Image (cartoon, rainbow, N blue to C red; front, top):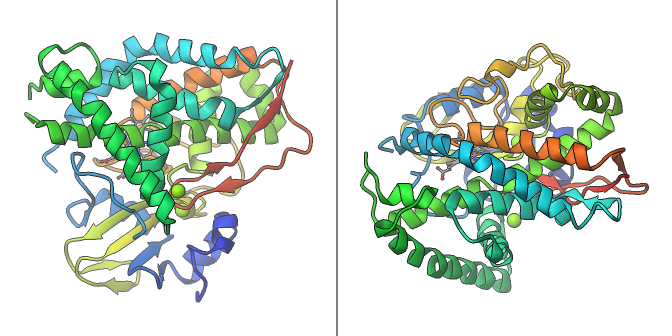
Length: 384
Ligand code: HEM
Ligand SMILES: [Mg+2]
Ligand SMILES: [Mg+2]
């Protein structure tokens, strides 16, 4: 009400405030910006579904601080689509290879020891980049990610964030040149050789930069969240162990329960009616994905993790018509929706295979972090 959704208070537990929010301030104004925060599922869904009214940035336009088209989406989605079938044995090696230094101990941090690196490597194979360079890239990507996600930064952090993109630009630009004339099967090569959008070098760089940011954070977060909540509801865990075809459902319900992307920003092109209030001209609104997925008017007993819930719409959970809104909704939702599913299902399965008797480490302290994107700080697990 006179509360704030950027505060340390909110950032600590966003779910503790969602009910109040859609019940008495469904169009919550913030002081800093200059932006409105929208909590009611119906209002959120309406916005995503209507891009002509609620605009976002183009795929080929750069990163910008979040807080402070011509339809390549299809074309790109088809590419990501032809890709996954030759990439699947590579997602598999990655998983297997990165877990291998931990099996001996019977102890890992799924977030830090495995997740972040895993996600980076998968995106690297998509882009066709040499995985010897995985540490350079994972570092550079955080700089950029931080400059995007953060409210405020220190002079040192901004310095490091600009150094990071300077390095990526200098790293990826000589590759675009290489593959403009000697293409392969990788995503960069396909972007270079069209043949449907005849993109320039600067544009391609921007595009893959966006693919890099998009396809990386949400993957590891999801894996960690799903494993945490499966383990927090150990008898759901046992159902999953006993039938692996449930994994996709476990994924979806995690996406619902605790969406990785917590905010989808949009900007108006026209004075429009949203909920009850009237919002003016061309200012920005934030779709509170977390508020939407917990809405009693969208899901029954919505604050209950349940992978067997009848109103999940599994048949649709990984497309434009998903009931949950973790990928967004409509013709502008996640482009890598089919890819994300396949990835998380594969990793998940390897994890459960090689980590027999997985339990949460004792005195592990579950804690979440981030406003725009959000995941566990750590996930300390013990296994045979
Ligand atoms: C489960 C993991 C993921 C989640 C929760 C997620 C979520 C999202 C969301 C909420 C958006 C904004 C959609 C909108 O504007 O309505 C988005 C955009 C996007 N996603 Fe995903 N995503 C995931 C994984 C991936 C993966 C693995 C890929 C690549 C294969 C990918 C590719 C993209 C791309 C290319 C965009 C466009 C961003 C831009 O236009 O700059 N995503 N994603
Ligand atoms: Mg940050
Ligand atoms: Mg939210």
